[PDB]
Image (cartoon, rainbow, N blue to C red; front, side, top):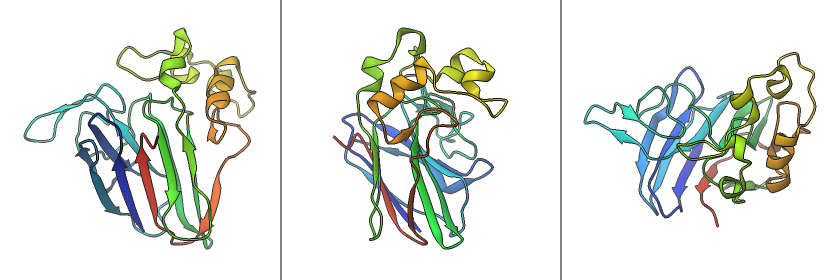
Length: 206
């Protein structure tokens, strides 16, 4: 499957793509404002994520640090990134269908649109100013708006027991971005697409 990753932000981002135990394609790349990066993701990939990292420094060997979404200090991510990270999430070719969503369960750093470029389903978007409106206790100094599980580490926010409800913090993310997951047991906002669709992830779509 082809993913085109487009940075429409006015600032540089470092895109990342991983399935948690391995890079997808090259795993990461710098995207200046306006740049597009096309990756290929193997059919059947389950649990892939794409995200943006902000304020990164890397040396000539690809090793460094980012203020949001850092994946163990590597330019080419093999593991998932440190919150806060707005997440584009996907599982491909699962019994004939692709499943896509955007999640704020690990916080929010950059606004995002995640849309098919082939026919047969709709896209999803979270483009509200979540960082600007972020509650004081969730603001991350490096930038971004953390989720409450990252900040407070309770069974309720992290849904550790498999039972949890919405909270004052999850309802904030949900009020600004109804089409993104706001906590682990949120009513799903997953979109079902035809198997083997292609997609575009756009940072700062507005």
